[PDB]
Amino acid sequence: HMCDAFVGTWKLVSSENFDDYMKEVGVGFATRKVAGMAKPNMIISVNGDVITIKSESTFKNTEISFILGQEFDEVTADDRKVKSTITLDGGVLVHVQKWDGKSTTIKRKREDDKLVVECVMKGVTSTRVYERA
Ligand SMILES: COc1c(C)c(C)c2onc(C)c2c1C/C=C(\C)CCC(=O)O
């Protein structure tokens, strides 16, 4: 029952500073433009210890399945090959991606009826807000 409040189907309703975050990460111009247009749905489900987060958009689909605390391979929407570890910290899903000696952290939390996602690369943060679909 860990992540019960995250489970469901969510749609993107606001984004702030995602272009600057993508620049910080190293995403190129064309990908930033097309990815920044997308309005993904995110589908979160849990089966035993396995959490699955799917992102469906016009830009890309993606899907990750993982066990908390257990590192996995992830190919990101922008085609980085990263090593990811996702934990729960005080009710927040904390997702660290490591690649090429770099690191970024993505935090997902429930706030009121929203799922709020904060992406941080060095000093740059982006906030993306999702509502139930
Ligand atoms: C941040 O990693 C990226 C990137 C870099 C780019 C270009 C992207 O383009 N499309 C997606 C989807 C996407 C993502 C995943 C987003 C997140 C893991 C959280 C924000 C959200 O779920 O909205």
Image (cartoon, helix red, strand yellow):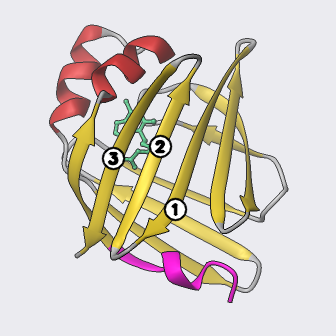
For marks 2 and 3 on the same chain, the one whose residue lies earlier in the sequence = 2
In which quarter of the view is residue 12 placed? bottom left
Image quadrant holding the C terminus, namely bottom left
| Crowd around label 1: few <14 · some 14–19 · many ≥20 (10 Å) | some
CB contact under 8 Å: marks 1 and 2: yes
- Measured Cα–Cα span from mark 3 to mark 1: 11 Å
**Mark 2 falls on what kind of element?**
strand
In the rendered structure, find residue 118 and report the number of the disc placed on it: 2
Q: Specify start and end residues of the magenta stretch as a single range.
A: 1-9
User: Is residue 26 visible from the viewing direction of this image?
Assistant: no
Residue 22 appears in which quarter of the rendering? top left
Query: Does residue 124 appear in this view?
Result: yes
**Residue 97 at x, y = what percent?**
67, 34
Q: Measured from the top left, where is residue 73 in percent x and y?
A: 71, 42
Residue 109 marker: 1
Relative side of 31 to 79, left or right: left
Q: Quadrant of residue 41?
A: bottom left
The three-letter code of the residue at mark 2 reads Glu
Amino acid at the residue labelled 1: Lys
The disc placed on residue 131 is: none
Tell me where residue 11 appears, x and y as whole percent.
25, 64
Q: Please determine whether, in this image, residue 27 is positioned above or below residue 63.
A: above
Q: Nearer the viewer, residue 21 or 42?
A: 21
- Looking at the image, the residue that sits furthest to the right is 70
- The residue where tag 3 is placed is 128
